[PDB]
Length: 264
Length: 264
Ligand SMILES: Nc1nc(N)c2c(n1)CC[C@H](CNc1ccc(C(=O)N[C@@H](CCC(=O)O)C(=O)O)cc1)N2Cc1cn([C@H]2C[C@H](O)[C@@H](COP(=O)(O)O)O2)c(=O)[nH]c1=O
Ligand SMILES: Nc1nc(N)c2c(n1)CCC(CNc1ccc(C(=O)N[C@@H](CCC(=O)O)C(=O)O)cc1)=N2
Ligand SMILES: Cc1cn([C@H]2C[C@H](O)[C@@H](COP(=O)(O)O)O2)c(=O)[nH]c1=O
Image 1: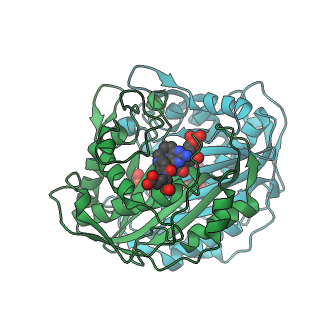
Image 2: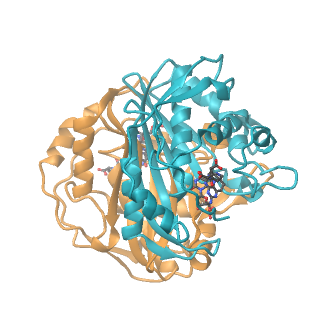
């Protein structure tokens, strides 16, 4: 996508060498922002093939409040295998914080239901926010949240959303993350009778791993194709009642996949 | 400052007219980012005189972990008077979360102590974060945090910081917010023997109140002047031992102050 390849070129042109946990080695910049108008098309990267079925199933899993990979395995999705413990558990990562953030006084807050009711009843609110950054539970999580905090906004009948991503593997993780939140915006907008607005992506430590550079330059040699279109085929009674089959992506004509090694 | 005046002009030109919680009305945009290289100068707005007395005391108050305005009054700082209760209390707002975020199990995390230890021990970490957005205590706060989340970053011996501000009064609040976090960067860099890098400001709902328009037009007619330089006159034993007398701003030649009514 034009904005995504510009970001890749910016990391390459302006980034600095940085180690990670012992680890692999990165090139990193700090601070970036880009905007996808979702009325232009669904922002699924076209300069390499991406696995949308995994994106959809992961988001439905988050929305259920699940943090065990059993559901993902029942749908042949392996993207979390490397972080799960021997029972398939990840600890209280995204889905648990979204649906049941634990308070100090024994309550749990369903932030997704909260922002659905704000969008329906108080869309001018300046605090329609979901955070996964539960400081007091980070030590129980298999990974600290990368897509850590997000905010919705309504204007002119359109729903927008801004994500703060504190750490971002630009080659492997970011295509998935963009498509995931874009999908969530469409579902929310459907539930609240709004049109889609912008997805605004903001990055903290935004980096390319050193073993992804030949793959990154291969992708950069390619011309983006027209964006695909997202069609939702049903209006479920709640944001938690969507099914994989309710979604169809039309016109996705990507360049070939590019394989790259994960950095656990 | 150039970037600040460009943002003000952008809200005027592109902002949407919104009813807000106060009944005042705003012009608002969603999603913006600015970057201040702290080696170019300290980013204190020069197109109106900003009073650093209140900024410094409020930051020292945060760092104490204090959420009662008594300390502020003892120093003739009144910026929190409206929202406090008859005892001076604000609930568990910024100071409490920075210094003693409560876990669900009755422990606490000192996020400032943690960040100092990360900068000194693990400066390449991608999770050097302080969050005031404690979902489970928002109900107890007098006001939901506006400067909600910030992240530090170290590259080539320089300390950078990025703030996510979910709601931004561009005219009254933003000059203070920028200066406050720029000051914290200088203080942490001093304690960690680092040089200062960038302060990156990221906004969510970024707005101008409808009774600030005369003041905005006045300020947009003024040419910015070269930024001042911050001097810290003493190095304290810790980030928790600074005093107002430690700070000097040299070469600050602002245009006159501009008075505007605050939306409660
Ligand atoms: N209107 C208002 N302005 C604030 N700055 C502000 C507040 N309320 C709530 C308390 C706390 C106190 N800090 C201050 C800071 C500066 C002043 C002030 O009036 N200074 C004058 C006098 C100088 C002097 O006396 O020496 C001068 O500079 O000459 C007063 C209070 N802040 C800060 C806070 C909040 N907001 C906004 C965004 C939304 O408009 C709204 C939230 O509303 P909501 O939850 O989104 O619905 O507060 C921000 O944009 N940046 C934030 O850091
Ligand atoms: N170092 C590092 N990199 C990351 N990307 C990363 C982590 N660490 C920690 C945990 C996660 C989980 N989410 C995801 C991680 C990776 C992918 C991913 O690699 N997608 C591939 C093919 C997917 C398939 O069909 O199985 C393709 O799109 O081609 C998708 C989601 N992300
Ligand atoms: C879950 C997830 C991880 N990641 C990457 C970011 C980091 O490189 C790495 C997280 O490790 P970290 O805790 O050291 O930042 O995984 C993404 O980029 N997007 C995602 O959604």
